[PDB]
Image (cartoon, rainbow, N blue to C red; front, side, top):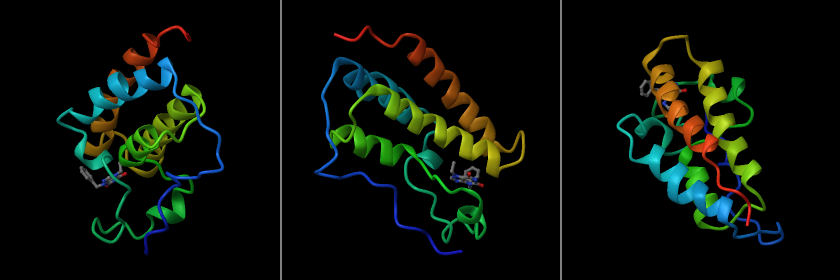
Length: 127
Ligand SMILES: CCn1cnc2c1c(=O)[nH]c(=O)n2Cc1ccccc1
């Protein structure tokens, strides 16, 4: 029932890049999802205490959320786009595993995911 430490968002010894695909992930993908009306549950790590989800971290071993991804993008955490695309996919998967089909949180994730898949379809060519 306690919250774990958050996912890592700073590591000076992790090598990094700034790249046109990573810039697209921030300016197009993250921004598009973040401004959506259903973003709010996904904008920060799950607070299992606040939300009364005492089993959440027993089930979900690789937590991920858009607050973390926004910090990873803004803090230049990544080496490549794959890593950031994987974070989005982990966030959606976690929601589909934890919750019941058709629960409001699930519909919310499916709506975000639709937009995510469209933007990823459109990923720019690597410069
Ligand atoms: C996506 C992470 N997350 C944030 N809040 C959540 C969840 C979750 O997986 N399951 C949940 O039950 N809630 C609570 C919640 C349900 C419905 C709408 C809003 C918040």
